[PDB]
Amino acid sequence: ESPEQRATRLKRMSEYAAKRLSS
Image 1 (tube, rainbow, N blue to C red):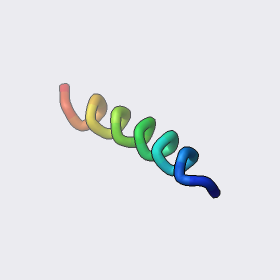
Image 2: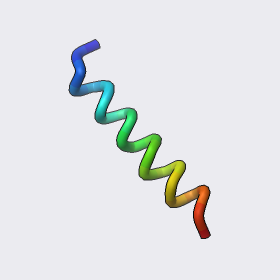
Image 3: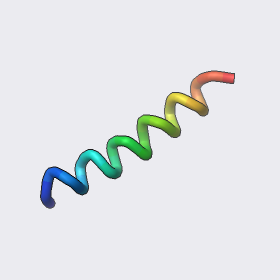
């Protein structure tokens, strides 16, 4: 569970949540 994996899943979930949230 390195810090890299955190940013990866975090970024994907973020960019997704953002794009999705907006419209």
